[PDB]
Length: 233
Image 1 (tube, helix red, strand yellow):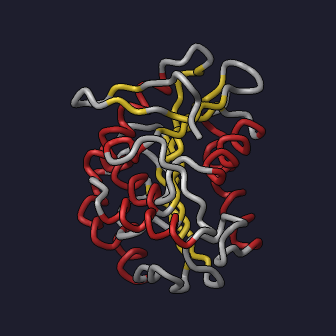
Image 2: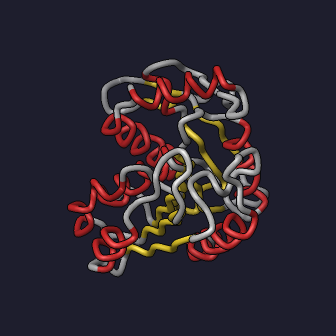
């Protein structure tokens, strides 16, 4: 689901929709939520509601609009999961980063914005959160179980604003990243903060997941919220 009428233009004229949550009280920092491989779906809507209940405004852009606008897949439906994997395999990461850039610009300019923008991304969005942190488009970025991070470690020195990452220590469908490669890579840049959840694999923060771990979800969520709080007025 998306907020009807919202249209954000990106770097090449491509336009995409977004699910927008206005804050309970204005002004407030705006959090751009980078979707997982299921599109802007029920978990994404829950994340927007959660952040609004925590004092933020939130914008979840339709990153799948370059392939199939308005895609919102049910992770519990096998055929929709297969569609999610197909869309993910065909996903253009650099274009995703450019769309998130455009969504951040949109976020900074909303009437209720306090001028501060953060980004929170999940697995598919988590990898995007790191790429966005390397570009430096947001004040603060957070990535939950970002896929393929070990491959992007050469970008560690480019991160100039804080970025926090929650890593599942166990393999599930996607393997867990190398604890060693990531810890060493991130350690060189104190603007990067990483936490490991040894009793969880990816998708641990989503209650609809077979990989949901309440204790990991809650601790990660508390770290995310403490990490985003400085953005608040």
